[PDB]
Image (cartoon, chains in turn purple, yellow):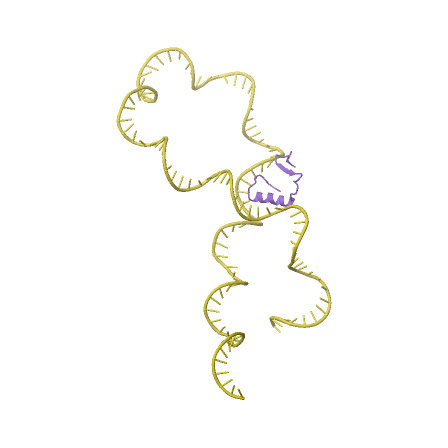
Length: 48
DNA sequence: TTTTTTTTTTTTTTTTTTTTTTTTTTTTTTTTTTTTTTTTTTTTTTTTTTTTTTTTTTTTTTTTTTTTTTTTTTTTTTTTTTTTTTTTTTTTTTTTTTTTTTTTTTTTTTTTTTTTTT
């Protein structure tokens, strides 16, 4: 369960993951996202 | 009772190999330096009515040099073949899940002994 929050003051967008699937480790999920960002397999991510 | 044959581990130290300490080259990483975006206000630029004298298009006619034109022979175009690259099925390998089998390490505290350095 995630939403693309859109700022009102500026046009920048931030994705917020409210919930996570079952039997998924959050630390490994964040590490995998960081690995994809470093390898440029997923584009558009600014921060994490 | 004396004397004779044979067997191996040691005096071994040297040759071969292995193990363990080393430091050149392409791939990371922190720094400074240059591209981007948002506000203030500011003289400055720029949008929109009115008048005006202008200078280019439309009555009409003229020609000549680009539009007609036909035809020879080139030469770009197309065909077949083969190589190089791109891209996707296929396979392999690895990781995570939850109950099982196995293990392995770092320090305090005192007192006494080995074990090196001066």
